[PDB]
Amino acid sequence: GTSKLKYVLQDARFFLIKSNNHENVSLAKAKGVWSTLPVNEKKLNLAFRSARSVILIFSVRESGKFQGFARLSSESHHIHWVLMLGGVFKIDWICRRELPFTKSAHLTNPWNEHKPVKIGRDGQEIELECGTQLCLLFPPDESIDLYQVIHKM
């Protein structure tokens, strides 16, 4: 179902994460971690303290798709990334399935000039309504149990 997912997303904040290669997103899916440049690190740490859930929505450059989304479970703290980096965020994946950009063409992001939500620099914040609808478009990931994520909120 979608009900626990909607609960996790209620009043969340959303950020677009752009990776230049699939290897880094694979590492993040395997190890439950993400790292970003300090300008984005500072924004994510501020957001983590400010909201019930901070959701990272991942897209590999040139792939034409999102590769999934995850919830921050920690601030950054001080991984063989394919590359100055900041700390390491621990994340819990909510969906490890892909979503093609063709399916999100009706969603615009007011915080990026109402451009389609696929468009944005690494770290671009996605407004609440747009980000919620974007996450709800992903195919359900039946391997994930949101019970454990709910308890961390």
Image (cartoon, rainbow, N blue to C red):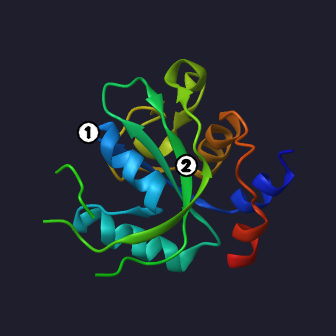
Judged left or right of residue 82, residue 4 is right
Please tell me whether mark 1 sits on a helix, a strand or a loop. loop
Categorize mark 2 by other alpha carbons within 10 Å: few (<14), some (14-19), many (20+): many
Q: What is the x, y in percent for residue 66?
A: 48, 34
* Figure quadrant of residue 80: bottom left
Choose between 41 and 69: the one closer to the eye: 69
Residue shown at 46%/70% (left/top)?
90
Q: What is the x, y in percent for residue 51?
A: 60, 72
Residue shown at 54%/73% (left/top)?
73
Q: What is the x, y in percent for residue 97?
A: 59, 37
Quarter of the image that includes the C terminus: bottom right
Which numbered tag is attached to residue 20? 1
Residue shown at 43%/76% (left/top)?
46
Amino acid found under the numbered disc labelled 1: Asn
Quarter of the image that includes the N terminus: top right
Amino acid found under the numbered disc labelled 2: Phe
Choose between 145 and 152: the one closer to the eye: 145
- Pointer 2 residue: 69
Q: Is residue 111 above or below residue 104?
A: below
* Figure quadrant of residue 22: top left
Categorize mark 1 by other alpha carbons within 10 Å: few (<14), some (14-19), many (20+): some
* Figure quadrant of residue 102: top right
Q: Is residue 21 above or below residue 32?
A: above
Choose between 129 and 29: the one closer to the eye: 29
